[PDB]
Amino acid sequence: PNTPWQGYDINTNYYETIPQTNVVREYWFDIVNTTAALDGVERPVLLVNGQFPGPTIEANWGDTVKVHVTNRMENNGTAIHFHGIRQLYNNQMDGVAALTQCPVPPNSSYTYVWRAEEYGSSWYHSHFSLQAWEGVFGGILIHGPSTAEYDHDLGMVFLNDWSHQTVDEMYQSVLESQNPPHFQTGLINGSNIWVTADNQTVGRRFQTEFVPGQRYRLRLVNAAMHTHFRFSIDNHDLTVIASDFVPIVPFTTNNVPIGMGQRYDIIVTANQAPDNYWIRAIPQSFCSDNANSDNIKGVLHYEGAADNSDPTSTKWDYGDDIQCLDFSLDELVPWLALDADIGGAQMAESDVDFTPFGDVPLYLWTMGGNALNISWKDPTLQQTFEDPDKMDWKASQGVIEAAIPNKWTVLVVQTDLPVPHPIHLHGHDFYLLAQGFGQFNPQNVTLKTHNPPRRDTALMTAATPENGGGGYMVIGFPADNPGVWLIHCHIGFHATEGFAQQIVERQSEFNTFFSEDLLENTCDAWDEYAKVNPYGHQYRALAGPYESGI
Ligand SMILES: *[C@@H]1O[C@H](CO)[C@@H](O[C@@H]2O[C@H](CO)[C@@H](O[C@@H]3O[C@H](CO[C@H]4O[C@H](CO)[C@@H](O)[C@H](O)[C@@H]4O)[C@@H](O)[C@H](O)[C@@H]3O)[C@H](O)[C@H]2NC(C)=O)[C@H](O)[C@H]1NC(C)=O
Ligand SMILES: *[C@@H]1O[C@H](CO)[C@@H](O[C@@H]2O[C@H](CO)[C@@H](O)[C@H](O)[C@H]2NC(C)=O)[C@H](O)[C@H]1NC(C)=O
Ligand SMILES: [Cl-]
Ligand SMILES: [Cu+2]
Ligand SMILES: [Cu+2]
Ligand SMILES: [Cu+2]
Ligand SMILES: [Cu+2]
Ligand SMILES: [K+]
Ligand SMILES: [Zn+2]
Ligand SMILES: [Zn+2]
Ligand SMILES: [Zn+2]
Ligand SMILES: [Zn+2]
Ligand SMILES: [Zn+2]
Ligand SMILES: [Zn+2]
Ligand SMILES: [Zn+2]
Ligand SMILES: [Zn+2]
C-alpha cells in the first residue's frame, strides 16, 4: 500500500512467495585487524571496515543483496555467514568454512550473492573459528510487513558480553579446564562504561532518546560469546512482535530472554513520565559468568531532558536472573500459521556431551557421538563434487542425511549435563516441537505440531544440578533446501571445539546451485596462503588451539 512490497502483507507465505523488486543492494566489506576502546579500554579487535557493530546490511523484502567481502587481515582467514538467511538453492553463499567454501585468505575476496526471502532482523558474522567474537559481525535489517505498528525504527540493538582480553587470548585456558569462560563486562550496541583501579570511569553508556508518546522498534540481537541475556527497560513495557525472522502474534512482557544468535523485534512506547530510565542487559547466571551483570546498562533518555544525569529507576521485578530460558512454546505464535507435519518423518537423536581428549586434556563438546573434525582445505562441497554419490562419511564429520525431497526430519538434541545451549540450524526455519528439562521420554512428552513456534535458533534448556541436570529440545524441518547445512551450538567456543553437525540435505541435487569456480578460486588462493603463512594451517591436534573447522 505505497510500500516496496505492494501486493503482499503479513499473511503471505514467505517460504513460497518472494516479492520480485528487481533491486540489487550492494555492500563492500573489508575485514580488518585493528584496535578499539569500546568501553574505553584499548584491546585488539577484528572488524568490518573499522566499525563495531559492523555496518548494517539494509534491504527491502525480495531484493537481491550482494556483499563483496575482502580479507585485509594478515593471520586469519575469513568466511561470512548471513544468519537466518535461508539460502534457498543458494547453499554455496551461506559462508561456512569447511562446508560450503574454503576460507578466504588475506588479500583475496569472495562476493556473496543472496536473495532477501524473509523480512525482519538478523546479522552476518564470521563463521571462521572465534572471529565472529573478535568483532566481525553486523546487523541485517530486511524491511517488510509488521504484526503491530510503531512510529520509528531505531534499528539493531546488539548485546555482547565483553572481555579486555581477547576471545582468542582466552581460548587455550578455556580448552584446558572444564569451567566456563569468565567475562569482565558487556556492551549494548558496542558501548559500556568501565571503571577500575583508581575509581576512574572510562567509555560511555549506550543512549537513545524517545520523544514522549512515540512508539519505537528495537531489533535485539544476542551477539555475545557465552552469555544468555534477559533484556528490559525500567518502567516500560515491551511488545514482542517477531522471533528471529518470523513475525509472531504481538504480546507484551517486562523482559526479553534472549539466546545467543536469536533476534527479537520489540515495540516500545514512550508512555512513561519523561525522565531517565535504565536499559538493562543482564547475564543469566546459570549459563553466564560475568563479573559485571549489574553494570551492563544504557540510558533511555526522554526528550524532556534531565541531561548528563544517571537514571535512578528500578529494575522490573520479574524473578531471578539465574536460569537460561526461551519464551515458552505457547508465548511464540507465528503470524503465518503453518504446522509441523511430522507424519512418518525420519526420527533422529543427538547427544550433547563434554569430554576430555589427549594427555593434556582438552575438553571438547561433542554432538551426536563426535566432536566435529573437518577440514578448511577440503570442504564437504568439494568432497561431494569430486565424489557426487559419496556415502562414506567419517563420523567425525557429524553427518545427518536427509536425501529424500520434502521428507521431514524430527531431531532430538538432548544432554545429561546441567548446561544449556542455543541451537541454530542453517538453511531453515525449524519448527520447535518440544523444549524441557531432565531426560526426554518420547512417551511422556507431547510434541506441539499445531502452528508451533518457528525460528532458526532455540535453546536446549537444561535443569540445574540440584534438580538432576539434563535437558532437551526437539525440532522438525522438511528437506526443502538442498545443500550441506551446519547445525550447531551458537556458543563460539563450543562450536570450535566440535559442537556442530552437518545436515547433508538432498545430495543428488547439489548441481542445482554448485559452482566449481566459486569453490576452486577461493580454495586455490587459500592453499596459496597456507604455503607461506603458518596461520593457513588448521590446528586440529590436542596440545593447542583446536579448530573443528567451522
Ligand atoms: C546500533 O548500531 C547500528 C550500526 O552502528 C545502527 O544502525 C543504523 O540503523 C538505522 C536504522 O535502520 C539506519 O538508519 C537508516 O539509514 C539509511 C542510510 O542513511 C544514510 O544514507 C541516506 C541516503 O541513502 C541519508 O539520507 C542518511 O542521512 C544517511 O547518510 C537510510 O536509507 C534509512 O532509511 C535509515 O534512515 C542506519 O543506516 C544504521 N547504520 C548502519 C551503519 O548500519 C543502529 O542505529 C544502532 N542502534 C541504536 C538503537 O542506536
Ligand atoms: C593482527 O595484528 C597483530 C599485530 O601485528 C597480529 O599479531 C601478532 O602476530 C604475530 C604473528 O603470530 C606475532 O609474531 C606477534 O608477536 C603478534 N603481536 C601481537 C601484538 O600480538 C595478529 O595476528 C593480527 N591478526 C590477524 C591478522 O587476524
Ligand atoms: Cl561450560
Ligand atoms: Cu549465527
Ligand atoms: Cu546461521
Ligand atoms: Cu553450547
Ligand atoms: Cu552458524
Ligand atoms: K597445494
Ligand atoms: Zn521498515
Ligand atoms: Zn562453555
Ligand atoms: Zn525536540
Ligand atoms: Zn536531553
Ligand atoms: Zn506431509
Ligand atoms: Zn562414487
Ligand atoms: Zn494444526
Ligand atoms: Zn595457485
Image: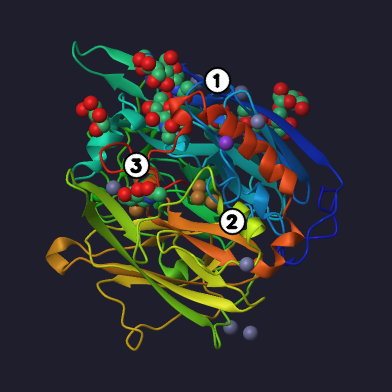
Q: Which disc, if any, is residue 383?
A: 2
Question: For the residue marked with disc 1, what is the amino acid?
Answer: Gly
Dividing the picture into quadrants, the one containing residue 338 is bottom right
Q: Residues within 10 Å of mark 3 (few under 14, many from 20)?
A: many
Q: CA distance from mark 1 to mark 2?
A: 36 Å
Can residue 369 be seen by looking at this rendering? yes
Mark 3 / mark 2, whichever is N-terminal: 2
Q: Which residue is mark 3?
A: 546
476 left or right, relative to 467 = right
Query: Where is 524 relative to 401, above or below?
Result: above
Residue 265: image x %, image y %? 55, 50
Q: Secondary structure at mark 2?
A: helix
Residue at position x 51%, y 55% from top? 240
Residue type for callout 3: Tyr
The Cα atoms of the two marked residues, 1 and 3, are separated by 28 Å
Which residue is denoted by mark 1 in the rendering? Answer: 50
Residue type indicated by callout 2: Gln
Residue 372, position as x, y percentages in the image:
40, 55
User: Mark 1 or mark 3, which has the lower sequence index?
Assistant: 1
Q: Secondary structure at mark 3?
A: loop
In the rendered structure, the answer to whether residue 5 lies left or right of residue 159 reads right
